[PDB]
Length: 290
Ligand SMILES: N[C@@H](CCC(=O)O)C(=O)O
Ligand SMILES: [Mn+2]
Image (cartoon, rainbow, N blue to C red; front, side, top):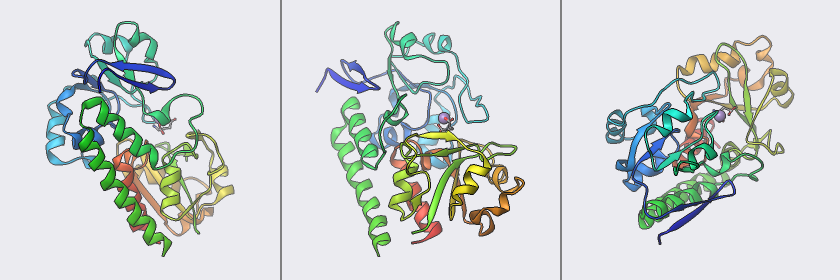
């Protein structure tokens, strides 16, 4: 049903038909778009698109989608200007990098969508329903509702299988380390990390933090001393990601470090809510067992 309105971070974003000139400023949408078969709607991309996320054909498609840049900062944030984006005359931009504003894009007729749990301000505790609701939204946006419904059903079944196995409690945290040294950031109950950990049978040590992601010191993580750690990174060498934690002075005081109960995985296997979050759930479950 078009015209379609999507409410996004409080804003009504209206589409008279499916978008045809999309710029991807984040990798999250690709997990759903490749299943719906709508990658031809993407004209440009920016940032990292790890091939580990995708099937071979999708990776070949991405190599043929030109890039507006790949420079990330130490927190994995894309560096790109609003003027560069506007110059391409897109009809839809997915993601808002630092310093790129919804208002600036909307002012010249460009629609903007952000992943709902990355809206500024409170978004409430995240669940696997946030994966499914976003897939159903993409189903409407691209007029692929039947395909979206089949994707949701397949994912729900896989999540149910992990939760059943678990039904037949260790603590955990998910972090985003700083390369060169530092535990960096942790994920609270607005992150996809939170329901991922809980569905895998863990207690999230930051379950009571009503934030998505927040800075932590080693001392902070030590006070929680989670049995297990998951370390995320947008790209680059996972050895350096683990070293950013385990080679810190005093880090051997961590149970997870002593027992080597540490999983390093690429960002979208946890955050934000996408089909890849279900892959991540399975990975955590198979790695640390139940
Ligand atoms: N790119 C990571 C780093 C944390 C941050 O945004 O500061 C995230 O979005 O979760
Ligand atoms: Mn970030």
